Amino acid sequence: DFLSVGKLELPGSMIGAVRDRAIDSGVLAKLSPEQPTIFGPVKGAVFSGV
Amino acid sequence: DLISPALGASIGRAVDLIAFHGIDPATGKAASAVHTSLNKTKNIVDATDSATA
Image 1 (cartoon, rainbow over the protein chains, first blue to last red):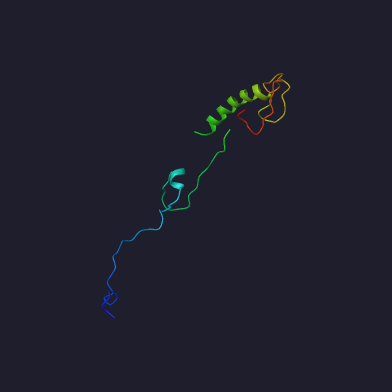
Image 2: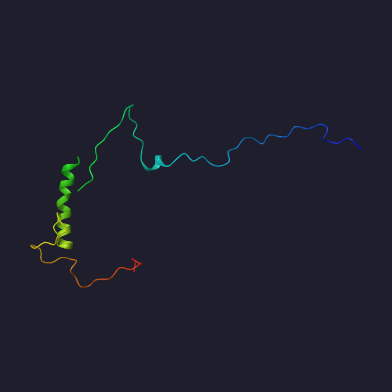
């Protein structure tokens, strides 16, 4: 027998903390702009056209 | 903002429709006061899958 490295149980090195994939936050920000109103059931009238 | 401009375009579409199909823009029936349209030409080409050609 001899004196190995497995006795010491040396701590490893931390690479860091990384996400698996890029974050998908949605697409409705590009298509239609946000219309921020106050709290309450919002209503609106529309006309088809011609 | 809405009603008046739409009603204003409603005739601009009417003339364009009369000159192309001789139709009454109100009802999908052919007009009697209109004799000729740009649809009744004999130089027609049956559309295919190509569309480009």
